[PDB]
Amino acid sequence: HNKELQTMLKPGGQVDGDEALEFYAKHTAQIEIVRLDRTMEQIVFPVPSICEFLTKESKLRIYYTTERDEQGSKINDFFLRSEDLFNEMNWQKKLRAQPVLYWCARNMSFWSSISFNLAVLMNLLVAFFYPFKGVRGGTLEPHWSGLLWTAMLISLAIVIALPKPHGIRALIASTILRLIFSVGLQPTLFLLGAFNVCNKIIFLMSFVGNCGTFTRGYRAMVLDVEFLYHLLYLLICAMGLFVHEFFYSLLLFDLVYREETLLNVIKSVTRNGRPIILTAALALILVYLFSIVGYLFFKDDFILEVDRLPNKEHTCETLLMCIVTVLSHGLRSGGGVGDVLRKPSKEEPLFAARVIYDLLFFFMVIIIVLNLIFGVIIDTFADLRSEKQKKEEILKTTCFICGLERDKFDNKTVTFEEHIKEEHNMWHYLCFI
Amino acid sequence: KEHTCETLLMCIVTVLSHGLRSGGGVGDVLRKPSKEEPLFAARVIYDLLFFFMVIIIVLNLIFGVIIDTFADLR
Amino acid sequence: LFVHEFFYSLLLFDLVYREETLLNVIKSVTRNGRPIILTAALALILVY
Ligand SMILES: [Zn+2]
Image (tube, rainbow over all chains, first blue to last red; front, side, top):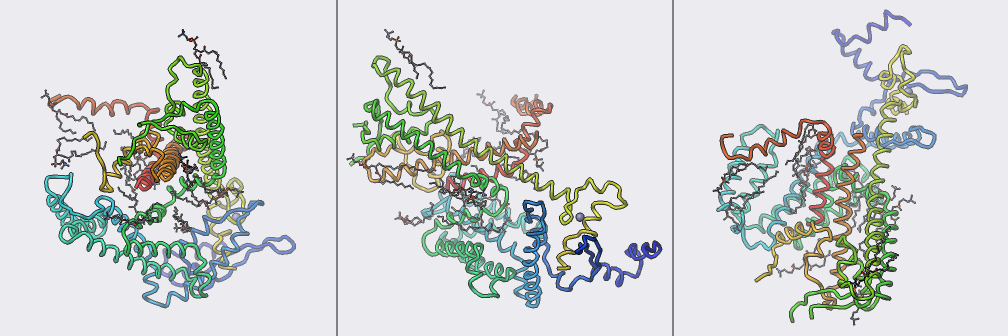
């Protein structure tokens, strides 16, 4: 009401009285509610001291992952997420006392990134030369020591660069390559495996630290799928350290499945999986009918050429199951079944029968069915892109709480961007709860 | 004499990238199982899994990404 | 002009990148390049 009073607590950023004014402005929220008589009134309250103990990553997760129900409102799931956020803030305040556990839980990204990187490098080491018979052999430059000296020069040039601006993995890779030639490769791989397993057993503690599920017991931490996945990763890492080496390749999926875009394209493939499975079943039954037709009428045309392992050049398939195997062999090769069956030679009476048989198989099975599978995949891309742009637009041009659109705030003595940060800020609603 | 073998697990990756082409899959370059060796069904499911999953799903994934980018741009 | 001749072929790209529709289709390819690179890496690990 007092315009003179209003214009001297707000612009207090440029005055010397900063402590009291910006402290009390920072620690004061504002919320609007509706009472029984459907009247809207405004409440000004102090924020709790525990509400500042909330990580902004969880805030972004709550802002993005909340979805609207059939009535078009996000508050119903927001309440449950608010309760979970309250428990998370309680555990964060409890955790902040410990100096070393908070240091481990504060740096999860470093442990995860270095584990991913050195497991990738471990897979690259086991992939290039498996039998571990030497390092001197190579189709590279005239000496392997030349490439080793080049790597040493690269490491020396990277050791005088800027402090961790770029090339941090380059010097480590050069050092690992230089250690590979000085000492035997199996000691180097044992050292790298021990480093990865100690990295994983400290990262598991770092993960269970800030995600404080383990303070309530054992059932909740055991039943968690993410903890089980991390434990499985640790188990197969220890198994690949102790018996043979291919389990690093096994955990390469868990490595490369950490980002979102590769996830999105794959998991679009796994979205409408039931049309894909049913189309595969349709292909199987079409192959079955074509195989029994070939068993009935073209039994002697199924001569195909094979080569025999040393202790005549042709085999026949007459069991109606080997014929299904041959038709699934001919489901590949693009042309169809006519590329594996013997050539009709234009003079046998079953020539036109062979021509229409081959053309029907090729056209109907190959074209229609394989194009059906690919059309299902493409349509799933279209559906995902449409719903993603729809939810992004409704998040960007609509208030989270009020649900009103940007078009209602044309002039109205206010703006939308101050409405959605002062009048209807949802973190003020969480603070009030 | 007219034939070579690849036993290094890197030459095998080279041969599998050689067989990532040719459309049919890896079953067109490997020798024919001749129906009587015990590892016949293992070869059949191996070839079918490689062809179906790798060829169909992955190459159709790349082309689907390209087509979806056309749709977004338009 | 001074050494060998194939650098005319090298500058043929700069020649054909002067219109707009070709640029539109090329960077329809290279707009979402990171899904394509990650799908290629997925193919590489499946081959492995
Ligand atoms: Zn509002």
